[PDB]
Amino acid sequence: SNQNNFVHDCVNITIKQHTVTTTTKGENFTETDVKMMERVVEQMCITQYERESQAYYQRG
Amino acid sequence: SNQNNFVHDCVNITIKQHTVTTTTKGENFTETDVKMMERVVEQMCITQYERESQAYYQRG
Amino acid sequence: SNQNNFVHDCVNITIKQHTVTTTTKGENFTETDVKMMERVVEQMCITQYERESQAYYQRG
Amino acid sequence: SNQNNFVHDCVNITIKQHTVTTTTKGENFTETDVKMMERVVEQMCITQYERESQAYYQRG
Amino acid sequence: SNQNNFVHDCVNITIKQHTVTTTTKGENFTETDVKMMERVVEQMCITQYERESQAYYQRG
Amino acid sequence: SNQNNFVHDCVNITIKQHTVTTTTKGENFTETDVKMMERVVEQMCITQYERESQAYYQRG
Amino acid sequence: SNQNNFVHDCVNITIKQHTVTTTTKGENFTETDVKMMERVVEQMCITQYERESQAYYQRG
Amino acid sequence: SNQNNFVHDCVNITIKQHTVTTTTKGENFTETDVKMMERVVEQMCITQYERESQAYYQRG
Amino acid sequence: SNQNNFVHDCVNITIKQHTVTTTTKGENFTETDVKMMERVVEQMCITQYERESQAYYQRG
Amino acid sequence: SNQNNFVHDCVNITIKQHTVTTTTKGENFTETDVKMMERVVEQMCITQYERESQAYYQRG
């Protein structure tokens, strides 16, 4: 019973909360951001499988 | 019973909440953002399978 | 009983909530965004299968 | 009993809520957006199967 | 009992809610959007099957 | 040109306004009184003119 | 040209306003009184004129 | 040109305003009194004119 | 040109304002009094004019 | 040109203001009094004019 496994998980995130409360009372507010997840992933993942394979990354 | 597996998961996210409360009381508010997920993924994933394969990434 | 598997999951997201409450009481509000998911995915995924295959990415 | 599988899932999203309440009481509101999903997917996925195949992406 | 499968799912979304309430009481409202899904998908998916196949994407 | 004067003014009130504005906006109000004059005078004035005259006051 | 004067002014009040504004905005109000004059005068004035005159006051 | 004067002014009040503004914004108010004049005068004035005159005051 | 004057002014009050502003913003208020004149005068003035006159005052 | 004057002024008060501002912002207020004049006068003035006159005062 042969079995090969080639697993690739570039990103893996897990949030588990039970109670999330937020309050923004006040009088004079300007430019209020109450986000929860802004910019999570900005990745690159290739997973090449054979020879003479190349990969060029640049984030200038 | 041979079995090959080639799994590729570029992004994997899991949120599990039970109670989410938000409140924005006040008098003079300007430019209020109460988002929850703004820009999650901006990725690139290729998964090439054979030889002389190339990949060029650039995020200038 | 041979079996090959070539799985590719570029993005995978799961939200599970039970109670979501939001309130925006007040007097003078201007430009209020109460969105929940703004810009989730902006990706590119190719999954080439044979040789001399190329891929060019650019996000200038 | 041979069986090949070539699965490709470019995007996969699942929301499961039970109670969603929203309220926007007030007096003077201007430009209020209470959307839930604004711009989910902006992707490109190809899945080429043979040789000398190319793919050019550009998001200038 | 041979069986090949070539599955391609460019986008897959599932919403399951039980109670959705919305209220927009007030006095002076201007330009109120209470949409639920604004711009879901803006994609392109090709699934070419043979050699010397090309694909050019541009979102300037 | 004789002239006698026996003036008696028990109460004398004078209101002179130009603009009176009132507003009772809201959501959940209970037992709101917006009167202007509730119980002005509760007096007693006699002005007896001859001898062995008596006056008995009691506000128990 | 003889002239006698016997003036008696028990109470004398004069209000002179130009602009009176009132506002009672809110959400949950209970037992709100916005009166202007509640219990002005509770007096007693006699002005007896001859001898052996008596006056009995009691505010128990 | 004889002239006698017997002036008696038990109370004399004069209010002169130009702009009166009042505001009671909020969320949860209970037993709010915004009166202006509650209990002004509670007096007693007699002005007896002849002999063996008596006056009894008691504010128990 | 004889002239007698017997002036009696038990109380004499004069208010002269130009701008009166009041504000009671908040969230949880209980038993708020914003009166302006609560209990001004509680007096007694007699002005007897002849002999063997008596006056009894008691504020127990 | 004879002239007698018998002036009696038991109390004499004069307020002259130009701008009166008051503010009571907050969250949890209890038993707030913002009065301006609470208990001004509690006097007794007699002005007897002839002999064997008596006056009894008691403020127990």
Image (cartoon, coloured by chain):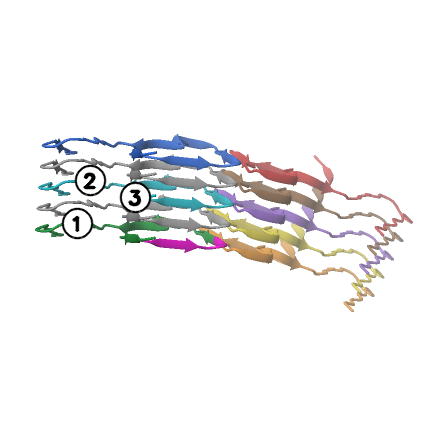
Chain colours: A green, C cyan, E blue, F red, G brown, H purple, I yellow, J orange
In space, the residues marked 2 and 1 are separated at their CA atoms by 12 Å
Q: Residue F46 appears at what percent x and percent y?
A: 82, 43
Mark 2 in CB contact with mark 1 (< 8 angstroms): no
Few, some or many residues within 10 Å of mark 1 (<14, 14–19, 20+): many
Q: Chain of mark 2?
A: C
Q: Residue E37 appears at what percent x and percent y?
A: 37, 32
Q: Chain of mark 1?
A: A
Residue ID for mark 2: C46
Asked whether the residues under marks 3 and 2 belong to the same chain, the reply is yes
In space, the residues marked 3 and 2 are separated at their CA atoms by 17 Å
Residue ID for mark 1: A48
The residue sitting at 87% across, 57% down in the picture is: H52
The segment highlighted magenta reads: A12-20
Residue ID for mark 3: C5
Nearest the camera: E33 or H48?
A: E33
The residue sitting at 40% across, 31% down in the picture is: E35
Q: Chain of mark 3?
A: C
Give the amino acid at mark 2.
Ile
Of circles 3 and 1, the one toward us is 3
Few, some or many residues within 10 Å of mark 3 (<14, 14–19, 20+): some
User: In the rendered image of this protein, does residue A11 appear above or below residue C29?
Assistant: below
Q: Residue A4 appears at what percent x and percent y?
A: 28, 53
User: In the rendered image of this protein, does residue G49 appear above or below residue E4?
Assistant: below
Q: Which SS class for mark 1?
A: loop
User: In the rendered image of this protein, does residue G17 appear above or below residue A3?
Assistant: above
Give the amino acid at mark 1.
Gln
Residue A34 visible within the image: no
Q: Sequence-wise, which precedes: disc 3 or disc 2?
A: 3
